[PDB]
Image (cartoon, rainbow over all chains, first blue to last red; front, top):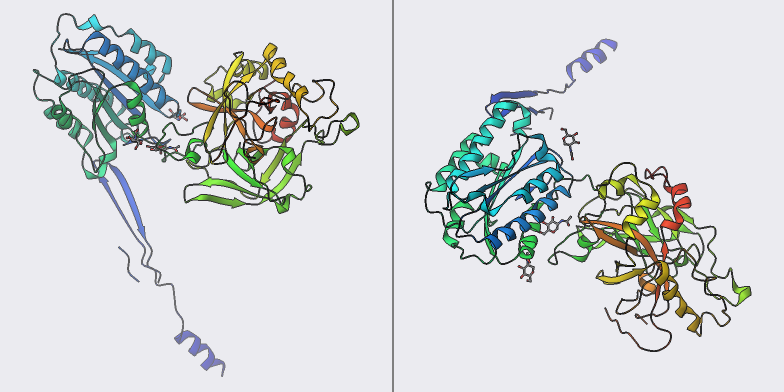
Length: 44
Length: 502
Ligand SMILES: *[C@@H]1O[C@H](CO)[C@@H](O)[C@H](O)[C@H]1NC(C)=O
Ligand SMILES: *[C@@H]1O[C@H](CO)[C@@H](O)[C@H](O)[C@H]1NC(C)=O
Ligand SMILES: *[C@@H]1O[C@H](CO)[C@@H](O)[C@H](O)[C@H]1NC(C)=O
C-alpha cells in the first residue's frame, strides 16, 4: 500500500513549466531588456 | 507638445528675428513675450536650460545652454534684456538658416561635451520656438536645416516627443502664414504655427503649449492660467466639506491628507467620523469622497463665549483642522496650497533661505490695499481687497451699525481682533455661509498662497445668484488671519510642513 501510494504520487505531479526568456540588444538609442513569463499560455 | 516632467532635462532655444522688416517696437513686443515665456517655464521648477539667439543676417548667440548660467533664471532674463535692436545694424536682412545652423552647431558641441551614449544627452527633450514674421529671403530654405537637426537627434516615430518646433508671429506684423507652416510643421493634430496680435493671446496659447500632466511633484499654487480650463483646475486646492448639519462649507488642501476650514462649520459636535469631504478629481466633476481620520478644533473657539456681554456670536479662533482618511492622489484638479512662513512657500516665492514669518507676511501684505481672491459656491473666482494698518480700523468701524447679531456692543475690538482681515469695501464681493471656510489666496510669481480663511461677514448675498444692497450696515467681510495663528498651526502641522522661524 505504501508502494502504490508513493508510485501514484510520483506519477501524478506537476511543475511550474516556466519558460522565461530575456531579450536584450544595443541599439543606437541605448540598451533595453524585456522579460516574458510563461508559467501558465503564450505572450507577445 | 512640451512635456513638463521631472525626468530628463529641458532645453528651450528661443530665436529672435531682428530683421529691418520687423520694427524696433515689434522687437520690444518680442522681448516682452519672451520674458513671460521664460517666466512660465521656470515656475514649474524643472530641469530646463534656456538659450536665446537673435538673427537678422547672422546669428548672435546671446546665451548658450553649454554655459551653466542657462539654468539660472536671473542670468537668462538679464541677457534677454541685454538684447538691442541695433545689434544687427550692419546686416538687416532675414536669415533663418543661419539661426538654425547655429542651433545645430550648439547641439553638436553639447553632445561632444557630454557623450553620445551617455544618458545626459538621451534624457533631454529639445524645444525651439521662433517669434518671426517668417518672410525669409536669403541664406537658404530653413527646411533643410530643420531636417538637419533631425538626424543629429535621430527623429522618427519613436522619438517624436524629443523635438518641438514652433513659429509664431506676435505683434503688428505683416505675417506670411505660408512660411510659418513649413518651419512649424504639424505633428499629430497639434498646431505649430500661430498668428497672434499681443502677448496675452500668446500667454493663453502657451498655456496650451505645456503638458504639465507628466510630473507629480505637486508643489503648491500651480493652478491653471487659462479661462478655457475648469474652475477646479484653476483652484485645485478648493475642497468641499459637508457636516451632519446638512450645510455645505468649503476648504483648502494644504498637503496630501490635511484640510483647513473654519471651526464654526462644525456645530453638531466633534463627531468627525460623521463628516464627509469632497476633493476635485479629474475622473468626475463630482469629485472623490473621503472620510476624516481625526479633527482638531481651536480650543479658544467658542461662539457663545461673550454672550455675557451681549455678543451672540464671537468668531475668535474660527479655524478647524481635519485629517483625511487616505492620502489625496495629486493631479491637476487636486493640488495643495502652501501656508506662508514655510520652506515650501519660500521655494514657491523663489526667496533666499534665511526667511522669517514676519518677512513672509511683509512680502505678501506689502500694500495698504492688497487684492485677494476667494472661491464661490459655483467654484468661480472673485476679487476682494485686503485692508491693513490704518484702514484696517476703518473697515471694522461698521460693525457697530449692526442691529441683529450684536444688540449690546460698545467696543469694536472685542469682536474684530487682530485675527480678522478686511474685505467687502467698494465693489468687493461678500462670501456667504455656503462658502465659509474657503481659502483667501493671493497670486504671485504664478503661485497661490492662502493668507486667510472665510469666517463671517456683515452681509449674506446667497440669502449662482448674487445681489448687493445699499442699506446700513454696508457689506463687509472678515477672514481669520493665518499669520496670527502660527503657533497652533505649527503645533499640529510641524510634522507635515517645515515651518520657517518666527
Ligand atoms: C535636476 O537635475 C539635478 C541633477 O543635476 C537634480 O539635483 C534636481 O533635483 C533635478 N530637478 C529639478 C531642479 O527640478
Ligand atoms: C478659449 O475659449 C475661447 C472661447 O471659445 C476661444 O476663443 C479660445 O480660442 C480658447 N482658447 C484660448 C487659448 O484662448
Ligand atoms: C491647464 O490647462 C491646460 C490647457 O491647455 C492644460 O494643458 C494643462 O494640463 C492644465 N494644467 C493644470 C495643472 O490643470
